[PDB]
Amino acid sequence: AAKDVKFGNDARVKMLRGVNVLADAVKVTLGPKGRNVVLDKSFGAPTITKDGVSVAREIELEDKFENMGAQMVKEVASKANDAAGDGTTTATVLAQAIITEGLKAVAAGMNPMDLKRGIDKAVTAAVEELKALSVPCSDSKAIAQVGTISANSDETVGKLIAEAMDKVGKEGVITVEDGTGLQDELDVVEGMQFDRGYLSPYFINKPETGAVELESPFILLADKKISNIREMLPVLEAVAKAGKPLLIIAEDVEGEALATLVVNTMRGIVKVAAVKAPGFGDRRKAMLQDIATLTGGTVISEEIGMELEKATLEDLGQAKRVVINKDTTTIIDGVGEEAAIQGRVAQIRQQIEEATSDYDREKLQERVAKLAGGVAVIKVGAATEVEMKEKKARVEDALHATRAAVEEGVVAGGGVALIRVASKLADLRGQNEDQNVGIKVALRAMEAPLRQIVLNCGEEPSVVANTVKGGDGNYGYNAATEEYGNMIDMGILDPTKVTRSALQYAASVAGLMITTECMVTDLP
Amino acid sequence: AAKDVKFGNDARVKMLRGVNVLADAVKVTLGPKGRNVVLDKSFGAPTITKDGVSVAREIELEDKFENMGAQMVKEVASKANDAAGDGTTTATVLAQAIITEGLKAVAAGMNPMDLKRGIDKAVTAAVEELKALSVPCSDSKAIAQVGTISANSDETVGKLIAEAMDKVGKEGVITVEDGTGLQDELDVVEGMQFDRGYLSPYFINKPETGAVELESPFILLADKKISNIREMLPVLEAVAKAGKPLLIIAEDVEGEALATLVVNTMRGIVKVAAVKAPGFGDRRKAMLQDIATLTGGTVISEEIGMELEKATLEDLGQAKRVVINKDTTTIIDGVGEEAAIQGRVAQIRQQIEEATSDYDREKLQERVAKLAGGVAVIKVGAATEVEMKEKKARVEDALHATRAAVEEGVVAGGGVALIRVASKLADLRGQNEDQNVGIKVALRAMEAPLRQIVLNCGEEPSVVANTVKGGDGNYGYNAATEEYGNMIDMGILDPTKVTRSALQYAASVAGLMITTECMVTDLP
Amino acid sequence: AKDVKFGNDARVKMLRGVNVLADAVKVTLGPKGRNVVLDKSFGAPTITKDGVSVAREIELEDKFENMGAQMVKEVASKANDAAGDGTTTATVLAQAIITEGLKAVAAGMNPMDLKRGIDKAVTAAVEELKALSVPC
């Protein structure tokens, strides 16, 4: 539709207002004295947040040329959350600083393209330096500290996440749920578990608890739905002669087969459990084949012509114990080989090297949870539902942030390591003065995380900067107790991944934005 | 619907503001210190760009007489991209300059329509001198230099495109797309790869990679959906009597055919595989004949009644290896009779040369890359999505400009060769003085590219223009390092294809526009 | 009964005010230079080529742009009120140092270290203008 168009001043001044209006709304949450933001929603009622990406995602403005600034910095705020959960405010703080301090250089008249080349050379150096400084985390105390830092001084949530990690290990899986009590809970399962259970309740043999018990059973697995007992009888008569209970994981069970299996249990002939296969789409076939290699069984797949009408006792899997309700099943210790189970984990772990989506990185980790270091779940504990919202953020995005710490490592916190790598790059040269100033725009923002924590405290940012830059090593200032010392032993370390990624996304959005000489939009 | 109307003065005054609102925006990105434009969007991330055709394509006004002016310069910007790729800003800069210098003649009192009759003869002269001067761009440093310049002074993109041309050849295929790196990656392909993955996962003989492997197979080529093994059995028995693996490349393979092929594999009888129509529609039949020439095969089709029931090992194609994954099939050399391959590959080069659209140019150029030449793909290295978008854009059209610089050649750049043809045509004359002023409209515009580069560079346009006119030939001003020398040595080359196109479309739009004595359009 | 304005909006008004006066004073400079006319409405307009004329007789209507014009009513006049000549020259130099210094103050440099840099340059330039002088 019909446009307005704005150049130079009228571009960069509107852009600067829009960037600062968005950034100011995000800035107010950072550190131990960092505060909260309220977001209204016409779909029901408001929600309180402490995260910058929640705030940034909601904004859109009346003035088109300022809306442009907000809609650009919305991308760096998402790129932090989409990479690591946390670091969203930090990335926005760095972005607004590299934008403002680069616009200062562009308006002083340094070449916008050599300013970008100088920012880029500083980003490369700072990324390699943050790798070189990346601790070497391994003790569960450092894990609990990065958990309590992200959960915002929460001893309990940091201890809960870190003890889940200490228990399930480097390649178990921890998940999270909208909770059921007025208190939090970690649940952990020392067995295989999945999205389905019984097709008839009359087989509950403990009315006291509601469970169906299968003591050291056989397990039969089929990709087809079963409708005639004709399809089972060859295995059935052999399993009766073998003297053991049986689980049938078909895709589905119906017809006369369901009733006749239920009657063979009801009248005391043989204990037979019918279940539907867990999940939907070929994720169902994948979990059926996971159970097969865990238990020592065949998968009878009708889609490749496999007659259930000739399956044997050799085609059965076995286990130490199985326990069933209507909608879930738990299996304890399947009879399949250690080398076959770890080879099963290796096949899933190979796909984790090429799992190019979020739902892939879910449905592949689902399958290592069931086999390797185990399955665990955090129930979000809260009294109010505005508290269920914020506590769930401080357990979802904080689990994603502690995972992000575990992969790349950690550095000396409150931004102090970012100031230390900035001090090492004080002597970093470009090719010309415009690139020297460009390097000295990117490095200029590396005090901003510390300065914005000290501003959230209500205290003087450039004072703490000029003490921190006098002292050496891990020397910094504790924003929660108001003393100077080693940041690590004062409790404070930042994850490498959130720091390093926030710096890149900030400098990327800034170095592509400060070069703006014209801005175009449809009429108001 | 009712009109507004404007004449002569009042027409041309509004039309000129329209021409400026387009072309003075498009101006702000040009040269080695060239800046950025941003395009506002409420739907998500705003579009940062450097490209004059994307900046032009947006522009639109509610003052319809300024809209008409802007839309005419939008056409020359489109014609630059749609017929040459790069030079979009250069065409737009030349358009407003030839418009300005032509309006300056119309308002001084020259015969308005004989200005086009003189401009067109000056276009002939300028196009023919640019052909007479056209280097012969072809060495890897010259290729890397035109890629460096088109990518906006990015030696990495220039080197990367040259390092792909180094494997695929002059007329081979290289594309670029969405990646996951913090640094770029090149994949390269010889033989043939095509869209269609494996039809069963129980064929994956490397759990470590996800790949299916066929060592020297026979290959059947079948234009009908094979639901039944019935039609295969005589050919299957002939291939069993040779002890080699099989692949069916068909319309489709399904039903009891797919099941029995997968079972004969899974039980350990013989590796016998199948895949469906590559691409979509009858691209089936078309590329199945290219596969037939590559493999040494006969194509069987049911639409013309071909009995598969009698085909032999001589009617089959063969390969050294075939490898299949989750999306694609790669033939690691089909056998194929070279005396037919070269004739068919030359006949595809014929079908490329006479191609009738961009979608034709695609589906024909693929067919030399997927045979004798090479295919290649750049997986984009970029942190943010604004960076993914800009990096893909700069690589996409530098990949266009590199070929454009080989096919029609190059001249000494930054407009310096354009200034050299301006000095060559001082004594050029037509049938009268109006045509002589007309010829001189085109020549007067030839300082504009240089002047707008030097203005983007923040230096004095009129000074560099008059010093460059004091020297001769390829001597010019390096607007990146800020100094005078040989433009060829410093990599500053204007591609003949983009220069020749920019001059033609600018002169054509201007020569039809400056004659405007009335304008008609609907009420706002 | 004051209006009052700070920062951004004040500096933007001050600049336009300086320009409205000094860009008129610019139209006359040199032998190929043009002329201006000014209404002494008590009897009739006066014709001129000079900066002290075009400064003294002008007074605007936006009060904040008028403040800019009134401040340069010293800098354009202090020429003819002490040195005789140089009215337009002083005005041309004044609007240039104002424009480029306000450009630096908008970019975000310290206004008083900008002054200390101007003053260091002026201190040298006053000696250099004697070093490049020959007597009359």
Image (tube, coloured by chain):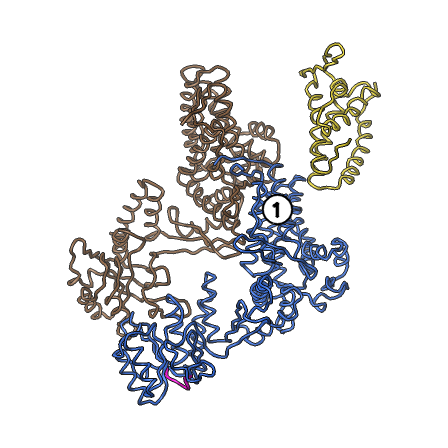
Chain colours: A blue, B brown, C yellow
- Of residues B86 and A303, which is closer to you in this image? A303
The magenta stretch spans which residues? A213-218
Apparent side of residue A111 relative to residue C125 in the rendered image (left or right):
left
Majority secondary structure of magenta residues: strand
Residue shown at 77%/27% (left/top)? Answer: C71
Q: How many marks?
A: 1
When asked about the image quadrant of residue B433, the answer is top left
Counting from the top left corner in percent of width and height, residue B371 is at 32, 53
Residue shown at 55%/51% (left/top)? Answer: A75
Q: The residue under label 1 is which amino acid type?
A: Val
Residue under numbered circle 1? A19
Residue B423 seen in the current view: no
Counting from the top left corner in percent of width and height, residue A60 is at 56, 46
The reply to whether the magenta stretch includes residue B289 is no
Apparent side of residue A37 relative to residue B8 in the rendered image (left or right):
right
Per the image, label 1 sits on a secondary structure element best described as helix
Counting from the top left corner in percent of width and height, residue B312 is at 18, 63
When asked about the image quadrant of residue A266, the answer is bottom left
Where is B198 relative to B40, above or below? below
The reply to whether the magenta stretch includes residue A216 is yes
